[PDB]
Length: 105
Length: 99
Ligand SMILES: *[C@@H]1O[C@H](CO)[C@@H](O[C@@H]2O[C@H](CO)[C@@H](O)[C@H](O)[C@H]2NC(C)=O)[C@H](O)[C@H]1NC(C)=O
Ligand SMILES: *[C@@H]1O[C@H](CO)[C@@H](O[C@@H]2O[C@H](CO)[C@@H](O)[C@H](O)[C@H]2NC(C)=O)[C@H](O)[C@H]1NC(C)=O
Ligand SMILES: *[C@@H]1O[C@H](CO)[C@@H](O)[C@H](O)[C@H]1NC(C)=O
Ligand SMILES: *[C@@H]1O[C@H](CO)[C@@H](O)[C@H](O)[C@H]1NC(C)=O
Image (cartoon, rainbow over all chains, first blue to last red; front, side, top):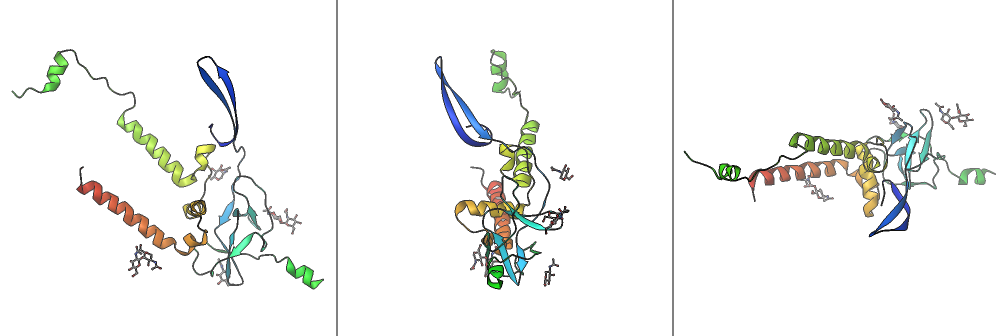
C-alpha cells in the first residue's frame, strides 16, 4: 500500500472500481555519520537496545533508526553481552551511570 | 537438407515478436537490485538509499526474527562461512542437476 512506510488508507468509490489513497512516510534529509557495532567499557561490550550508535566525529551518541535524535549513552538504553575481544569494530567510549550522582549526593 | 519446423511456422504465417526488454537489460535491473540490497538494505525500497555496513544490517535482520544482535557479533565468521558454503552448494546443485 504505497511507497514508503504505510500509515493510513482511505477508500473512494469509482465507476466499476475502487480508488485507494495511501498515506505513507518518506524520509527526506539524510546526513553522514560514523557508526560502531559495540562500545568497550570496563572490559565489557555494550550493545544498543533500540537504535544505532553514531558519532559526531568527536563524541558518541545513540540514535533511533528512522530519525535523528541523539541521546547520551547510559546503562538504561544499552545491555551488556560478553567481552571486547570478540566483536569486530568495537570502539572505546564511556557509558554514563545514573546511580553514581545520586549516590554521591 | 535437414529442414526445421521453424521455417514451416515461418512460411505458414506464424511469427514470433522479440521482447521489449533484452537479456542485457534485465541483468542491469537485477544488478541494481543486488547493489541496492547489499549497500543499503531495505532503505532503498522506501525512499533514498542510505548506506550501512553489512555486518550491522545483518544484526538488524536478526532482531526481526526474535534473536538478540550479540549472537551475530559473537558468531560472525561462522555465519559468513555457512553462507559461503550455502552459495557453493547452490553452485554445485545448478552445475550438476539440470532438472
Ligand atoms: C558533536 O556534539 C557534541 C555535543 O555534546 C559536541 O560536544 C560539546 O559538548 C559540550 C557538552 O559537554 C557542549 O557544551 C559543547 O557546546 C559541544 N561542542 C560543540 C562544538 O557543540 C561536539 O563538539 C560535537 N562535535 C563536532 C565536531 O561539532
Ligand atoms: C553450530 O554448527 C556449526 C555447523 O554449521 C558448527 O561449525 C562447525 O564446527 C566444527 C567443530 O568441530 C568445525 O569442524 C566446522 O569447520 C564448523 N563449520 C563451519 C565453520 O562451517 C559450530 O561449531 C556449531 N556450534 C557449536 C557446536 O557451538
Ligand atoms: C556522504 O559521503 C559521500 C562520500 O562520497 C558523499 O558522496 C555524500 O554526498 C555524503 N552525504 C550524504 C548525505 O550521503
Ligand atoms: C581500547 O582500550 C583497550 C584498553 O584500555 C585497548 O587495548 C584497545 O586497543 C583500545 N581500543 C582501541 C581501538 O584503541
